[PDB]
């Protein structure tokens, strides 16, 4: 489906601030944005809610849906499966809202190959050390997956500099500043959606 406004793809390393920024955006502008609820096989963290943060499913269920053709894209990240189902995006488009997707770098490259035509925004930590500090001060991950996520962060941090890959790169040093720059990147779309 290509009806509705231009979608927004938000990416960046684990722990960079994607969820925090998107939660703020959906709170302030709940009438114009909607969140694509991805499927994942990873376990929920305290406070996460099925059908809101993710559809938390088993690998068997995820695989059956993949085999059925139910996903726009999927990827393996730090030992678990993640994916954007067709219905997750179509539900937001049906409501005439701007669909916001939170995906990894593989997901960005996957979505580039679709007809979705989004704006691509990368959210970056000030440094890898701040990232690790932020990730560990949450400690929702095993050491093994913290290692994998810190490695993927470096690999994907470099690609944020790839010309033409992202439309905007936002360094999340101060959350208030990053959130202003998020809305700046979307200001024309927000104005159109409001009028
Ligand atoms: N500007 C900031 N300064 C300090 N800590 C932050 C900032 N933004 C987010 N955090 C913290 O960093 C952690 C990771 O943020 P999160 O939004 O979960 O990252 P992601 O969704 O990109 O994996 C969270 O515990 C959050 O409270
Ligand atoms: N490719 C892809 N990546 C996703 C999807 N949902 C979440 N991710 C990504 O998977 C990584 C891990 O997410 P987390 O486990 O921290 O919630 C993040 O980079 C996040 O953006 C998805 O549907 N598709
Ligand atoms: F989006 Al994350 F760790 F919460 F990469
Ligand atoms: Mg997150």
Image (tube, rainbow, N blue to C red):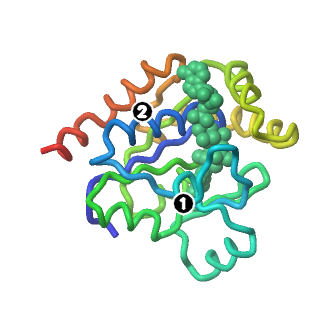
- Residue corresponding to mark 1: 51
For the question of whether residue 91 can be seen, the reply is yes
Q: Residue at x 43, y 43 (%)?
A: 120
State the image coordinates of residue 134 (x, y, percent, origin top left): 68, 25
> Dot 1, how many residues are within 10 Å of its Cα: few (below 14), some (14-19), or many (20+)?
few
> Dot 2, how many residues are within 10 Å of its Cα: few (below 14), some (14-19), or many (20+)?
some
| Residue furthest left in the image | 195
State the image coordinates of residue 65 (x, y, percent, origin top left): 62, 77
Residue 167 vertical position relative to residue 54 in the rendered view, above or below:
above
Q: Please state which of residues 80 and 49 is positioned toward the viewer in this rendering.
A: 49
- Disc 2 element: strand
Residue 175 vertical position relative to residue 144 in the rendered view, above or below:
above
Q: Residue at x 72, y 19 (%)?
A: 129
For the question of whether residue 104 can be seen, the reply is no
In the picture, the quarter occupied by the C terminus is top left
Q: Is residue 128 left or right of residue 172?
A: right
Kindly indicate the quadrant of the structure image that contains residue 160. top right
Front disc: 2 or 1: 1
Q: Which mark is residue 168?
A: 2
Specify which label sits upstream in the sequence, 2 or 1: 1
State the image coordinates of residue 30 (x, y, percent, origin top left): 33, 45
Q: Residue at x 44, y 52 (%)?
A: 35
| Residue furthest right in the image | 144
Quote the CA–CA distance across marks 2 and 1: 29 Å
In the picture, the quarter occupied by the N terminus is bottom left
Q: Residue at x 52, y 47 (%)?
A: 102
């Amino acid at each position: 489906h290509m009806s509705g406004p231009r979608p927004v793809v938000l990416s960046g390393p684990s722990g960079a601030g994607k969820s925090t920024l998107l939660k703020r955006l959906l709170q302030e502008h709940s009438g114009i944005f909607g969140f694509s609820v991805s499927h994942t096989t990873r376990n929920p963290r305290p406070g996460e809610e099925n059908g809101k943060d993710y559809y938390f499913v088993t690998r068997e269920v995820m695989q059956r849906d993949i085999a059925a053709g139910d996903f726009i894209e999927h990827a393996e990240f730090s030992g678990n499966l993640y994916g954007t189902s067709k219905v997750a995006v179509q539900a937001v488009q049906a409501m005439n809202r701007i669909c916001v997707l939170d995906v990894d770098l593989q997901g960005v490259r996957n979505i580039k190959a679709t007809d979705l035509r989004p704006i691509y925004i990368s959210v970056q930590p000030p440094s890898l050390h701040v990232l690790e500090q932020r990730l560990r001060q949450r400690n929702t991950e095993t050491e093994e997956s913290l290692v994998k996520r810190l490695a993927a962060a470096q690999a994907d941090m470099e690609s944020s500099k790839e010309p033409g890959l992202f439309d905007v790169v936002i360094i999340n040093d101060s959350l208030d500043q990053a959130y202003a720059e998020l809305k700046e990147a979307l200001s024309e779309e927000i104005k159109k959606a409001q009028r």
